[PDB]
Length: 176
Length: 176
Image (cartoon, rainbow over all chains, first blue to last red; front, top):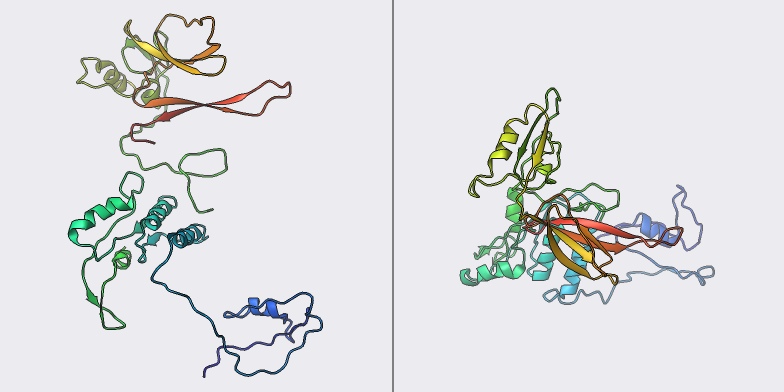
């Protein structure tokens, strides 16, 4: 058993810690904590009380199946990435193989004046690898800063010591 | 995003860059005006049968792009102008053949365009219909590149007179 972190919280509206920091449960959790958040009803809080409890575990957390993801989710994630207010000078593929996601990323890198490092599915043989590039839609005179890589090789994984195959954006960005 | 950089300026306060062009050259210079030369010639663009003004900066614009040695022997005057432009200004006069024509767009009462062309010298007249017509005068044939006209409505004035914004745009061969 390992303890992450503890803090002193209160259910009162204006309870203040001895150091002056706030102790209201939503503000206290949203200010200093990094793992949990809370929501408090605004009508029963005045008379609400608490007790002593031990080992309250979370049950029901599940991320579903990560193998299949809808294209709409990828589009929303790309749109979120487009609006992030930060410096980044290279957009990597990071494994997405959907054509629409790659097209949106290509639209991204031609708008911030940066350079992408996308790729295609490594399982494709040499014959059908060529049609995939124009299937992506990157080819043209607009997305002039991107680049497409292919890598039909199987290596030994660093963690599981198994025969796995993965793309090639990371090495290209490391070289850059 | 606030990090995006657009391509062509609109009306918002911002700084934008254009796509990386290759088939274009530039030159800079400051006029001296110690002794001005003059002389007739034959070129592309420019108002025919009217004295122009040529400096070391706008000679690529008012006098058009250079002609081609392959197309007959009409390439002499632009080379001569370049040779003597690195010293002072100029007062070249352009002359055109009789069969040279300039485009004209004429509008009806309902607002339907009707393309047409007319030779130089002759004044433009309007028939019983076709309320007003607008034509270019720079003399460029508008074949390479192409110039397009865009008309959009706008806010009326205090007296109630209708006003519409008129926009003239140029489309390059590539697509920009």
